[PDB]
Image (cartoon, rainbow over all chains, first blue to last red; front, top):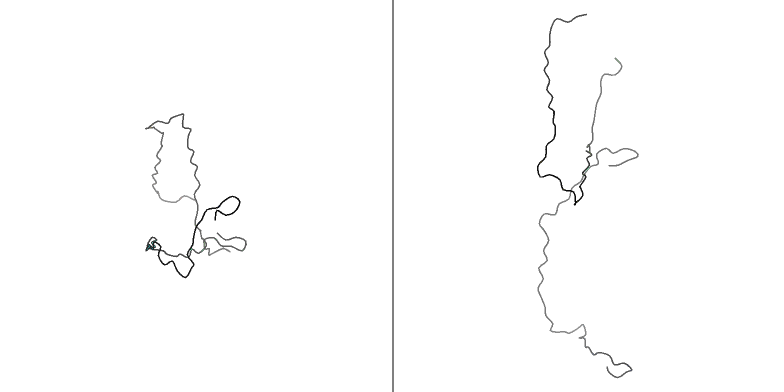
Length: 51
Length: 51
């Protein structure tokens, strides 16, 4: 690593097929209860407008 | 008459008002007094009709 010109820093990486260890943390996904959809039919529709 | 009869609608009506916040340096009283009038009606029908 420190072979060339200005020396560099070493790091190693495990290939994808194997870690096999790293720290595996269970992650509970949470979002607020009650997601609801409304259909607001336009008041005062026209032929040249929508409101 | 030519007209009889007629049909009237309304759509959602907005209302327009104007909030003016004031300058930090000048302070505005904690309690304050406004002049307010209050109007009432009294009707009394009479007979007979005049023509």
